Length: 250
Length: 110
Length: 50
Image (cartoon, rainbow over all chains, first blue to last red; front, side, top):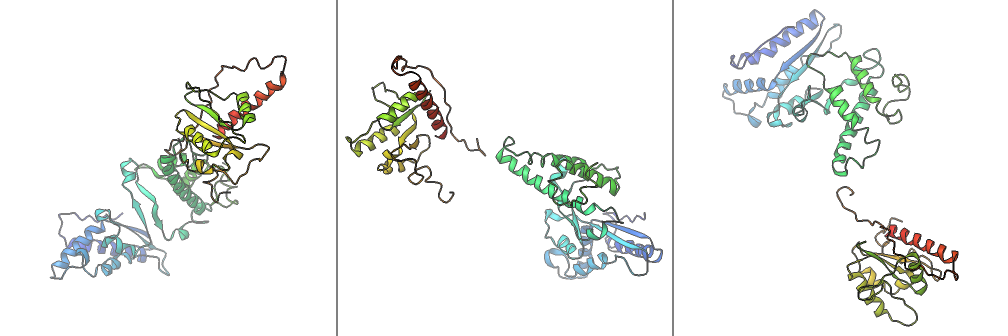
């Protein structure tokens, strides 16, 4: 680890050069020493505020909602210092972290970060108030390049199907828990009583992890199968039968 | 207990439903039936059905189908629920799915 | 109850105060007995339909 710490009472110009030092070091490491680097940048919103300050110091008229008109290019010169390259055995993976002001998804900073990056993870507030850690909402979250990261020879041959089935079952269970409130719990099917045990078990056993608990990918997939074995083999519709034969009977 | 069944058929049907066990006299000596033959007119039919409805103790009014064939106006105007009204078949004309006031609301679902 | 609506249905409390007990003990036996059995069951079935 190489840690670059910039504090809220530090000079506001150093906040402009902090991610560029981080990414210069990352590029050295990855493309000259051939390591696999992961770069985590916390609260790009503070970076945007410092950008606004040093812009207004140049006597430039503000832009849309406060931030300069060239904020897209400035964020892009940071997010695009990443990727694999030809002839070198190293990479750079980036994980920006933002706080959405007013929980708005169309504020300039989240909106422009969506045009440069591939996917998003959502840290939810209903899941945080219900005392779940980590409070990650998987329905709005997405990874645009998951199809490339998973599979045979990379994690395991059952990864995509387990993930698809967990997503489907979770959405269906949420809908079932919606209907339960108006129809009543004594007028539910037996297949709608399974989508309500999956919900509790999924949020308390799969999502909720523990701040010092390290689960490899295979432990994650085994937990997924322990959760998918609630339903009879005939209800798991999104898993091909050639895999329901190898991993279901355990 | 709080409500009694009630008939409007003919002599044979009211006796069949007395054999079943229904048929009652008011404390005013009014019956839970009004037998109809070649004698009485339809105004009697309709005000009898009216005093059947407005009577606040009757729950299930049975009416032979061939009786209701010309007083469809009296029973189609009935739109509440608890004064239940069933039309009954017999040998003269058996049950016809057309002239029903409770299959009235099943338009399309057939 | 159905989804919050209260559908009204009927309970058939069976009372017993049979007045038709004479019914010609020696003039009409099993015949009328099975006849009233039939028509009482019919009464209950039409209660269900109501």
